[PDB]
Length: 279
Length: 303
Image 1 (cartoon, each protein chain N blue to C red):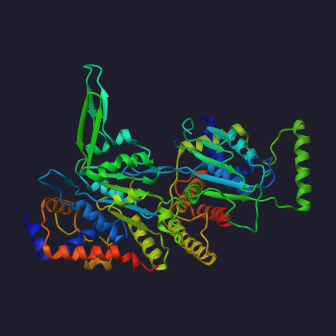
Image 2: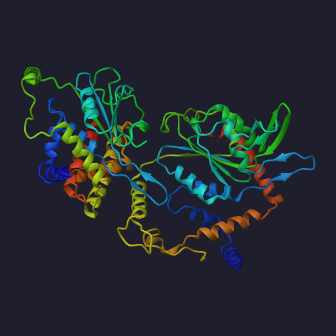
Image 3: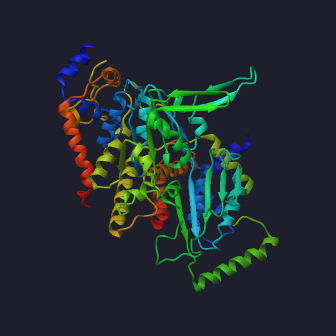
């Protein structure tokens, strides 16, 4: 009973999103957008039934593609550890409402999958044909992220220094950097938020998202028509459902009964940065 | 009865036009598919001969196209409307499920027959989604039903023949996932000649993203989504021949035309299925000449 007040105080702050994002794998350098996506996946959306008997998915699906050495398995392990229910496979029934991480991609479960390039390493010039999965299975994923080995002389030095500092200082002290939440506390907070309530969208946000979806569909049209080639990542109503689910998850993170326009804007920005860059 | 007679007499030639139009308001376009579904609902005529030979009176239609062209929606609508409609997915039911089997009863030691999926659906509709995922062997099993509508079973100590006069809807995806415009339809379909020949109609649906078509589809989907059933409070968690006009379901432009109600449509379909037509001599020569033209079109197929 006492922990309810603690969770309410934690979720009533104006900076819950930043604290949660920083709490997602503080050891890993960079990937703030990836950390936020992982956090909103862990919070997840809300499922809704229909009187006709039909059900709509309330879980988010993410896919990651990149060269080896981009710390993909570490994120999967951290997600499995943090999630109240978590399964890790090398490539479903026992998981109910949890998260299933799937490495080497080449029942109410959220799916987080990692995969490698067809040729082993990404080729920027070739563009498409670097993903072997068919568009039919690619459409199920709510978001797709691409990671490339951005070779910078200063970035390698910074990464080496960060790794060596993590190696050295870890026996000395194990303390939060800046207000980071403990693993058990974050686990209980996520469970409490998931159990307590689930929000719904608003009319103005719905109209804004509809207009943005129409504009994005026209843009994907024009890109495909000018390129004279079929995009391996199509845009359909499932993308709109994914954006709605991400906005609902963002509203759920604040425990508000109704979603705001800021959540929809953040969901649209994340969806753009992931899919449009990937596509 | 009086209303049916009045509608038939007033709308003489428009019936087949209206029923196809009002078949599925929730689905936009695909007039030919709606006409084919209407023809399936009406059905053909089964003819029995003095020699006892049986001629099939059912029609088989196969739909192939890109994803998200409202094919499963049509299958579900047919399942809801048809009196005896059975859905059987590709790998959900095998040949044992589709074809009646023989089981040895331990209580008495005799062998009994248990009806399959198609045996129960006599003079009905069988819907098969993901027909591509079905194995070739179930296709061979279904071939007998599609040819003569009968299943012959013989296991030592017992033999029988069961009637399987039924119509089949089939929905399948292309081998490449999306239909290839450049490649020939033979490569895209990827099916044997016998199976295609046994099918009566083949429909190919393309997700042509035309400006006006995309705008119209989006408008129809938005209008259907924003619609709410009357008599119900907003935000709550949860017979005339012509349907009452709705500003959202129909639209302001569609005020000039009305859709037929579901119950009246079902009654008219049943009455029409009762009716037994007779072919005329004038149409026979025209049909024969057009068939000869179709067969000779091999030299006139152009590109």
